[PDB]
Amino acid sequence: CSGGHASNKEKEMVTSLFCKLGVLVRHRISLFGNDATSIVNCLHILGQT
Amino acid sequence: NPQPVDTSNITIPEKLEYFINKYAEHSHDKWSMDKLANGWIYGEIYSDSSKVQPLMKPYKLLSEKEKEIYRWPIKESLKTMLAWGWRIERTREGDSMALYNGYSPRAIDMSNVTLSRDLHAMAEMMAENYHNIWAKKKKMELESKGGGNHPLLVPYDTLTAKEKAKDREKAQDILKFLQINGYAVSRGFKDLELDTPSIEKRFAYSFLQQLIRYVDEAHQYILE
Amino acid sequence: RDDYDFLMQTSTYYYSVRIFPGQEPANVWVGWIT
Amino acid sequence: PGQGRNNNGLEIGCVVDAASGLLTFIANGKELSTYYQVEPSTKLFPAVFAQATSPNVFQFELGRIKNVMPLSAGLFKSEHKNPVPQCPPRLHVQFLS
């Protein structure tokens, strides 16, 4: 309760991050130079966020 | 390379004349205290060997020609203090004492006078100006000499407590005498309006806006 | 100076408080409490 | 007068008349207008309420003025008729906690 409240604008734009990076990583693992693991980590933590 | 805040354009208001006075007087009083502690005596001739001082007469008996250059540091101090925009407000008891209206060895023990911590930051930064003025004049003198370097020429924060002591203590003594007079010193302006309701005002929103813009730029790169 | 007879027969008592220089007198109250 | 008082620290003097209950205050050698009249058998504790704006705030000066007993002559029975001001170890400053 001591703060730590993202606004609904925060949360909707975070969802925009998630969707747009999904669009990026759509079938581009070949282009990603083995950092595809970093993309996978990022999408997990975003899914939790 | 330190630039002192130039204040030649700025002029002092007439209401600060009453403050220029009694500080001419107080500096004369403390200077006379130092002289009498050193054994300086009221003698019409200014001979150092016999320790006779013609300046022991009260400020009213003092001549105005030596009152100049005397008032000079006080003048520049108040001028610079105003140059930041800082405002000072005079209280009624000042004008009450105004209309109220051999040497006099009474002095004020200002050590126990205490400013606030806001006033302390105020005094620290204006004293940093004072050290910058000294550094600029010494840099000019040293480049004119063409050879040498001074140990205290180092930057202000590089100076130590004892090295800062003179500059700080003169800063506090002037601002404290001001406070005890009642001239209410504060910063030049206060917050007109802060956009706290702004959702973008928070760090997270600006960070993620930059992030989405860069990642969309990267998106159209990746499409290319 | 002070009359010893009056001074011994009186019941008036006195104490004083010195507000040190630099301490704002507006923040200091002096007197008696029960 | 206000403002300058640095010639000597502000000396508020409290005068109590145990026979009449009159409480008069002396400030820098002049009587103040405010006076308190108390009822018999009231036990009055000398007290100072202060908010610290300096390392040195105030000082309980236990002395006497012309034609007045010091506070010790009223506090203590053994020193009832002794005009010399005193501060026995029993008397000490207490703070509300």
Image (tube, rainbow, N blue to C red):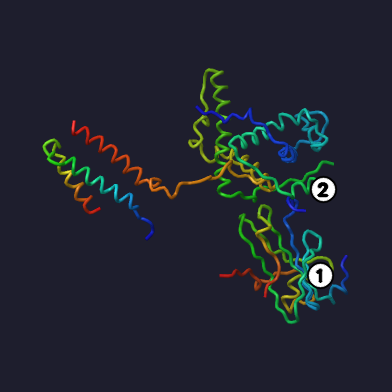
Q: Residue B118 has which mark?
A: none
Disc 1 crowd, CA 10 A, few/some/many (<14, 14-19, 20+):
many
* Foreground pick, B80 / D97: B80
In the rendered image, which residue does mark 2 sit on? B100
Vertical relation: D18 (above or below) B177: below
- Secondary structure, mark 2, is helix
Q: What amino acid is found at the position of numbered circle 1 in the picture? A: Val
Q: What amino acid is found at the position of numbered circle 2 in the picture? A: Tyr
Which chain letter matches label 1? D
Residue A18 seen in the figure: yes
* Foreground pick, D20 / B205: B205
Q: Decide if residue A8 is on the left or right side of residue B86.
A: left
Query: Nearer the viewer's eye, disc 2 or disc 1?
Result: 2
Give percent across and percent down for residue A18.
Answer: 23, 47
Give percent across and percent down for residue B37.
Answer: 72, 40
- Secondary structure, mark 1, is loop
